[PDB]
Figure 1 (spheres, protein in one colour):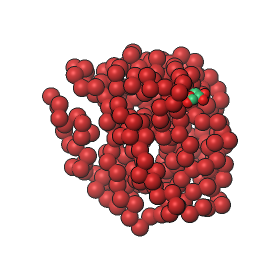
Figure 2: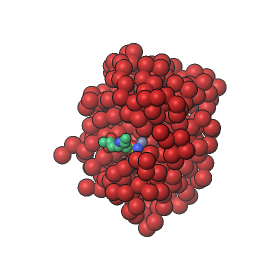
Figure 3: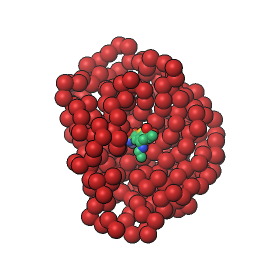
Figure 4: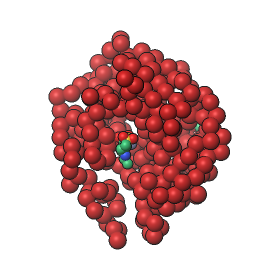
Length: 249
Ligand SMILES: CCN[C@H]1C[C@H](C)S(=O)(=O)c2sc(S(N)(=O)=O)cc21
Ligand SMILES: [Zn+2]
């Protein structure tokens, strides 16, 4: 399987031809019409555990994205979730243009990147909880992202792995006060096999990176071990909401 962009220069199955569960009815990502999302008072604050601890994370190019291995060293609870969820991995989706790098959209507005923090239910439509943050260009270098951005030139090819300098997950997120507002729905993984087992949370507040930090991703990373196709536009096309609803805090 591949993204649309990889087909043009392949030395593979494009998104509209993906099999498995990818052609089903409760798929992700979606466009969120914010006025159509109903406030649900049960969507309380998230509580984070291990997000404040400095770690040296392993980060790897898996041929589709760059992925930090979180190795169960952090967890979340609250946020209307039925149970705590263990953190498994963090990865991103991006482009090199400001309005075609996110997977989800808000009222038709797209962003430059989207970051996905993937967690698994501690014990189904909510086996996996993904925390989704939308990214745009701001005025300044986001210092919290510097260890990740700095690591990228050490994993230019698929299968490569490196160790980031000391950093926390908290360093990557908005101020906690700004995480109170989010959107919630049930959907799928955004890559094959597209399993309908994800409870999604899309935070309303964008993260800001400097333009140069966002461009680093497409400038330093490659889809192929021949380094001829720059990694970008790793974005699944929008899927239909159908008879689901979106709720918000
Ligand atoms: C390369 C895609 N990997 C898949 C399977 C992995 C086992 S996972 O962590 O479940 C996961 S989370 C997402 S996303 N884009 O919906 O957040 C995709 C993936
Ligand atoms: Zn993702």
